[PDB]
Amino acid sequence: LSFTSNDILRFDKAYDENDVQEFVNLCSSTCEIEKLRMHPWAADPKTIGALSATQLAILASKENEPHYKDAIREANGIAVFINLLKSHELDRVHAAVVALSFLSVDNVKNCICMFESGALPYLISGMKSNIDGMKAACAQTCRNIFVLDKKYKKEFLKLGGITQLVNLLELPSNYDDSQPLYTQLEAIYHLEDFILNDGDEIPEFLEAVKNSNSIKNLKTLQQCPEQDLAEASNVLLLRLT
């Protein structure tokens, strides 16, 4: 066949061998690939770099092989993904968000690494996206990080994270009683996890959530035709009132 880019050959070999470190090294590749879908909302990878980030996300998503989540951290993957978050290429940012969201699940070391490596401002910015999968994944990753340490919650608050979370409570502008309000319900739980330290209410953070559109948005949510959401909204509302 044809001679091809070294990066394409490196990718193909890394793929055959689940070579985590090589995939991380390849995330910086700008080698263009041909048009392809691999994921329900992430933009199609347009380079070997974004494609490598996507394969790493796939490895991180293997429930029955949690060891990949550690291998990826040890390969310096988290710093590499945070760098991709700075990209103006939609597929690079999306792939990094997907990878980081899986890496943050059931892996405290990874969450600590994400905090220490500066992920939060990018993830908080990501909660502003009009793409529901993106905003929900960013919100979940933020939560997985900030529940671990009061200082992480403080930083989240300082960076405007509560503003963005509270905004996730808002209904779509032409809301249709048929469509599920997953992200809204998850955001209720995120806010509770912010306020509470192992079941105990933290006064500072209670006040933070009070000083927002939370009560307004929650009042709107507690009248929706959905028992889980209506009940959850009622519960958090009572706490803030």
Image: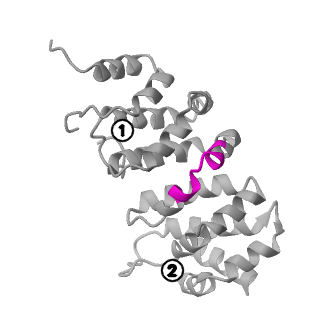
Which is nearer the eye, 229 or 58?
58
Which is nearer the eye, 200 or 4?
4
Q: Amino acid at mark 2?
A: Pro
Q: Tell me if residue 119 can be seen.
A: yes
**Magenta highlight on residue 121:** yes
Q: Quadrant of the C terminus?
A: bottom right
Predominant SS of the magenta segment: helix
* Residue 225 marker: 2
Residue at 68% in and 57% down: 146
Residue at 63% in and 85% down: 215
Q: Tell me if residue 189 can be seen.
A: no
Determine which residue is flagged by label 1. Answer: 50
Q: Quadrant of the N terminus?
A: top left
The number of numbered discs placed on residues in the rendered structure image is: 2
User: Residue 204 location in percent, x, y?
Assistant: 78, 74
User: Residue 75 location in percent, x, y?
Assistant: 56, 27
| Sequence order check, earlier mark of 1 and 2 | 1
User: Residue 5 location in percent, x, y?
Assistant: 24, 21
* Residue 37 against residue 11 in the figure, above or below: below
Quarter holding residue 117: top right
Discs 1, 2 touching: Cβ within 8 Å: no
